[PDB]
Image: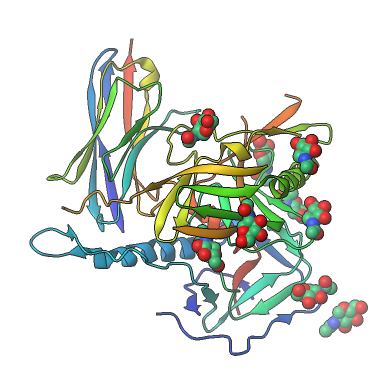
Amino acid sequence: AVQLVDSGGGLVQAGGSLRLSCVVSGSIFSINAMGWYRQAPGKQRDLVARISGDSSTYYIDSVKGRFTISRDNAANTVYLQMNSLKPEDTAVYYCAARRLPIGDYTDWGQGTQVTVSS
Amino acid sequence: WKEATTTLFCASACVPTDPNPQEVVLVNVTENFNMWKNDMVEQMHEDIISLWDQSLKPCVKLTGGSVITQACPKVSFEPIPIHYCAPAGFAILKCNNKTFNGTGPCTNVSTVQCTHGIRPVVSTQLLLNGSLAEEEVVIRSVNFTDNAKTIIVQLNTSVEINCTRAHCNISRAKWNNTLKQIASKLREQFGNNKTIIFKQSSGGDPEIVTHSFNCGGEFFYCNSTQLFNSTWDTITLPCRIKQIINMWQKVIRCSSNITGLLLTRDGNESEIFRPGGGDMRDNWRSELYKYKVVKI
Ligand SMILES: *[C@@H]1O[C@H](CO)[C@@H](O)[C@H](O)[C@H]1NC(C)=O
Ligand SMILES: *[C@@H]1O[C@H](CO)[C@@H](O)[C@H](O)[C@H]1NC(C)=O
Ligand SMILES: *[C@@H]1O[C@H](CO)[C@@H](O)[C@H](O)[C@H]1NC(C)=O
Ligand SMILES: *[C@@H]1O[C@H](CO)[C@@H](O)[C@H](O)[C@H]1NC(C)=O
Ligand SMILES: *[C@@H]1O[C@H](CO)[C@@H](O)[C@H](O)[C@H]1NC(C)=O
Ligand SMILES: *[C@@H]1O[C@H](CO)[C@@H](O)[C@H](O)[C@H]1NC(C)=O
Ligand SMILES: *[C@@H]1O[C@H](CO)[C@@H](O)[C@H](O)[C@H]1NC(C)=O
Ligand SMILES: *[C@@H]1O[C@H](CO)[C@@H](O)[C@H](O)[C@H]1NC(C)=O
Ligand SMILES: *[C@@H]1O[C@H](CO)[C@@H](O)[C@H](O)[C@H]1NC(C)=O
């Protein structure tokens, strides 16, 4: 199987930057796409960003220009750099990975809390 | 006789079976089924993930402190029917009500040692090469009042989808009649005067807003917008072939039967429905709904 660990979330102020890390371990050589979902208490999930095996990416319109997803091969990590953070970014973020060639994600992390004040 | 979870074995690695099976209806017996808490779905999801991982195993080489992408013979034929079979001390109950909604008591229940030949087909939005429903179209959900809970649709007339490389082809007449059937079935559960609206998926990631599948060893993503643009000569769906690349390792035509759908409801006087789901446990659950495992 696969184990994902989310980290990086915390308290920052509006206009600050954060760097969430998703560390990957186990039978990881079948992952063809990872991503970041976020959920705030009382709302539905939100796929905010995703990277594929061919290094193509997707971002929702709310984060286009402020967020960047990238891959660290030497560390088996996936980074989500969050810039120009807004109060509307406060939620629990989970990293996810897909081990099937298509469909929704198959593996999920424990989540990390991102909060920002104004 | 009680409900239980256990590891079924498989049959066609897997063990031989069916030189002559035997179905047996248990007379005067009604049994409660719940397709949404059926651990057979979890077992089959795990088995399919392991199937894909094993199919990818020969494309890697363990040289030095890493795994490298290698040879990879492309045409790796995946879908052959498998049967899940109860081990000693267990038995698989099978519902036979042709309009069973999956959650409730089946009055006509038979007993089997193995399920039917299930085709593990990985696809999104559309359910292909699956089983058909007798007489009527069936819709199934844990809670129709609860939107974002996936809606599994089983047709009775399959629709031919002929794809080549890169597009797919569906007849407008057959699909029109199919959509009319689905619309009436949804009117039954959501309101008679309520109007049904079919619109494109409400996501964003092009990996989930399309109908994706495996067509002859290559993976196709097809824009299915022409199918969900209705309110209640030949449709050519544009497609792109995407190459699956495993992130962490170091450096054409096919015809199918559309037999089902996966929908999600919005959330007025109307109801909007959009192709959704994505989770393959609902793909397998669309076929394992009429089964359950019990301990004797
Ligand atoms: C099934 O129900 C009928 C009711 O008419 C009963 O007469 C019959 O004995 C039942 N079958 C068995 C095997 O008990
Ligand atoms: C119960 O289902 C079996 C399997 O299709 C069928 O042969 C039988 O006629 C059914 N019984 C009733 C009463 O519908
Ligand atoms: C399925 O049909 C049975 C038979 O009436 C019913 O008891 C059950 O509530 C139905 N399931 C639903 C409505 O989710
Ligand atoms: C398929 O089911 C619908 C009910 O939704 C019915 O009107 C139609 O006649 C059925 N088709 C066939 C070929 O039996
Ligand atoms: C279905 O969801 C509604 C809320 O939309 C709730 O009131 C109802 O109790 C739910 N029913 C079941 C069986 O979960
Ligand atoms: C697919 O091909 C079969 C025969 O090859 C034909 O009967 C069917 O109408 C075709 N469907 C489309 C959409 O072209
Ligand atoms: C297709 O369905 C529409 C309703 O959405 C209907 O008006 C039209 O007559 C149908 N076409 C055929 C050929 O049945
Ligand atoms: C599909 O085509 C329609 C119309 O050209 C367009 O609005 C939609 O964005 C397309 N979807 C994809 C996934 O290409
Ligand atoms: C459906 O089955 C046909 C033949 O049985 C096969 O050629 C086709 O690839 C299958 N489609 C999928 C999506 O597996």
Q: Is residue B243 visible?
A: yes
The residue most toward the top is: A118
Q: Residue at x 83, y 32 (%)?
A: B193
Q: Position of residue B39 (x, y in %)?
A: 52, 63
A72 horizontally vs A60: left or right: left
| Rendered-image quadrant of the C terminus of chain B | bottom right
B293 horizontally vs A51: left or right: right
Q: Position of residue A34 (x, y in %)?
A: 32, 43
Q: Position of residue B178 (x, y in %)?
A: 72, 48
Q: Is residue B260 visible?
A: no
Report the front residue among B26 and B98. Answer: B98
Report the front residue among A6 and B133. Answer: B133
Which quadrant of the view contains residue A7? top left
The residue most toward the front is: B233
Q: Residue at x 62, y 43 (%)?
A: B235
Report the front residue among B197 and B37. Answer: B197
Say how many tags the image has. 0
B44 horizontally vs B131: left or right: left
